[PDB]
Amino acid sequence: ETFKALKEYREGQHNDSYDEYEVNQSIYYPNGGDARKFHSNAKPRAIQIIFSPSVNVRTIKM
Amino acid sequence: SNRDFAGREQRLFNSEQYNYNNSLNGEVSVWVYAYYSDGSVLVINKNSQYKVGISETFKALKEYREGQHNDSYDEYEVNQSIYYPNGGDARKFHSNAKPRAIQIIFSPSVNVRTIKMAKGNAVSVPDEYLQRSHPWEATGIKYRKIKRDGEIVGYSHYFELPHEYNSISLAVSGVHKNPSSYNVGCCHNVMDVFQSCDLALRFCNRYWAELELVNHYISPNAYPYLDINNHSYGVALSNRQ
Amino acid sequence: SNRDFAGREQRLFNSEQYNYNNSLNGEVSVWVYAYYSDGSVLVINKNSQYKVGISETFKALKEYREGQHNDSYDEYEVNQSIYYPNGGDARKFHSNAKPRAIQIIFSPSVNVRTIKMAKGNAVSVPDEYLQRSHPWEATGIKYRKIKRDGEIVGYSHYFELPHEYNSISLAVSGVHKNPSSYNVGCCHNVMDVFQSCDLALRFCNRYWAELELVNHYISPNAYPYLDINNHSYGVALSNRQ
Amino acid sequence: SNRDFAGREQRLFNSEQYNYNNSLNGEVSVWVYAYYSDGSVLVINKNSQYKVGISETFKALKEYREGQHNDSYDEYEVNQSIYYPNGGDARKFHSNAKPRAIQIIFSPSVNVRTIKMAKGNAVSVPDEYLQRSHPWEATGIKYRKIKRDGEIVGYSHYFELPHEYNSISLAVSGVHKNPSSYNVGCCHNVMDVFQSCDLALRFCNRYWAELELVNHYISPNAYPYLDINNHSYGVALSNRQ
């Protein structure tokens, strides 16, 4: 997944979508964007990766 | 030499400002800063003679973005589910409009031993139920000295609200220092204190970042501040050029 | 026997809550309930030491539905036609946002003889014209005891506004009981009462039905209430398990 | 002298970066730039081990302005009239959302003789009809060396779409250089190449101008670029300080 694809998207509701285009610009390069927030609440705070027990753990790559 | 009158007058002008603020004729001031997860900060300031404070509801401390969408209907529902568990029909687990932290700051003209805080729950009860509530706690011992160049420029109490259950109403209060034995609230001056209640000036605003707060609110007004990095701001004036 | 310490401690814990509230260290509390024709109810609550009250404009008591349509422009006009007959350009004869009834409730820690109400007209004049207005009426004799299990848990004043001309502003005030001869407002404690003004916590909310009010506001907080069926709510604590 | 170890280590650090990229352990990368009449540019980038490519539909290459109006219903219709003449009900002769030009860029770690392109028509057919389509053309001979300071920093294929009939789907593919006789896709490593398919990282974005692309995408990441003035960008690293 891309950075943008991992950001919170709320289906059928407002998403601050124009401002969040700008958030992205300021994430890709410091001071690159014209966003009206310091920290986007759409950014993931954590990640968990889970594999089925049928994986070989020594093959996992990230 | 002692004939540098520019130097002597500069030092006096600053000392006079320091001392005037600390006189019974001067201001006492309080600020509440509410810190939100998007990095924006709400400030509420009040400035008055004699005594000063601030009292806000749970809802009033929640992030409000002027002239933009605020999820306002869903946030009515968030409130209902905060006032009573499962009381609301909200489409989120955690409202990002809830303050993540609070900082209370007093001007150095406060008497720290007079500071009082009522930190209520979300229905504005200080301590679980009204029948068992003392209506304030004296929190002065918890205030840190905000210092610049050796000089106390302010007092800070900082507390996080990092858990889902930190949902608060808040009032704080302090009294202007008075080392005299003259009671400013006794019969000769009491109606002046009643007038001071009417005369107190309030300010509020939401800044997009702590950077803006520091650059455009704290610094231009020579206010005290302590930032999230534990760095002090303000201007030392006592016997200083 | 007298060796049932669980029983004795339960009774003391409750008696202590009763008595603490009624101490000079305790809360006094007031609620204004405004009842609308759609069955929803606005509550305003204030909780403070020493004395407490609530003061609202005509407009502030009108139904407001958070995050939904409110006929807001037409309701500006309704107001103009309420402030002066034929002063407005409203598209309705009677605004359903006007309160149909009011209930004032005080905690049992109030002294009923101190209760004061200023029930103004729509431009906030107590009695027709300011020049002839006493700024309050002492309404204590009109308060009914809200009782549970023999115990007074609160005091209620209920009044309807069933006529087209009942358009009001409203303020109410009461003082915490004090059977002592120690004046809490005299010179030794006066600045504490001034601080109590800053420290008072406010709450407001509109509930969709009296059922919600009873289930999710009155009951979980052990507050007193009297419903439109004349049924009492609250918790008796004096010498009770 | 030979005892300037800062100098020797600087040159090695750069040479190591050059060489690592070109190792079988390193990345191979491709970029598609689509140039629109309003001067904005869409970039699609993919970065992977072993081999890498990009495949897009006609519609996917059309200008999309995030969070703004896009004439989206009319542009559904534009598409219908592109897929079949007079198939749509569009209110324009020429959509300004259609790319005016394409540039394909590969990292210098590609083997140019492995580059393959399938430039289809608007219904994703490489050559008029599927029955007569070879599914790719080997276009390596057309790639220009992007050079800085003597060093090949990338490879460019640039082609305009200046006619009303240049309506394309597009896929491109290249393989990482491998001067060894070790086949990275043979049985000892084949499942690593299958994993590389999962592990490939994609990026896409629309920049308002080529200036922004150069300043904020190409330059900060030490990527190769050739601008519309035929000027080269990138960083030379082989045996350089």
Image (cartoon, coloured by chain):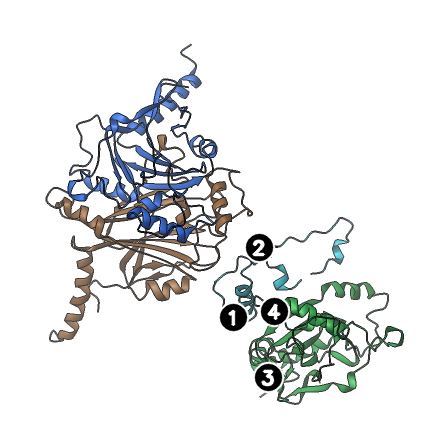
Chain colours: A cyan, B brown, C blue, D green
* Mark drawn on residue A33: 1
* Foreground label between 1 and 4: 4
Q: Disc 4 residue type?
A: Asn
Q: B156 or D56: nearer the eye?
A: D56
Q: Position of residue C37 (x, y in %)?
A: 43, 37
Outermost residue toward the top? Answer: C1
Q: Nearer the viewer, mark 3 or mark 4?
A: 4
Alpha carbon of mark 1 to alpha carbon of mark 4: how far?
21 Å
Report helix, strand or loop for mark 3: loop
Measured in 3D between alpha carbons, the distance from the residue under mark 3 to the one under mark 4, in whole angstroms, is 47 Å
Give left or right: position of C229 versus D67.
left
Q: Please report the residue visible at 27 percent of the width from the left and 26 percent of the height from the top.
A: C142
Distance of mark 3 from mark 1, alpha carbons? Answer: 33 Å
**Amino acid at pointer 1:** Gly
Residue identified by numbered label 3:
D241
Residue for badge 2: A13
Which structural element holds mark 1? loop
Chain letter for the residue marked with disc 2 in the picture: A
The span from disc 3 to disc 2 (Cα, nearest Å) is 53 Å
Q: Element type at marker 2?
A: loop
**Looking at the rendering, which quadrant does residue C238 occupy?**
top left
Q: Which residue is mark 4?
A: D70
Tell me the chain of label 3: D
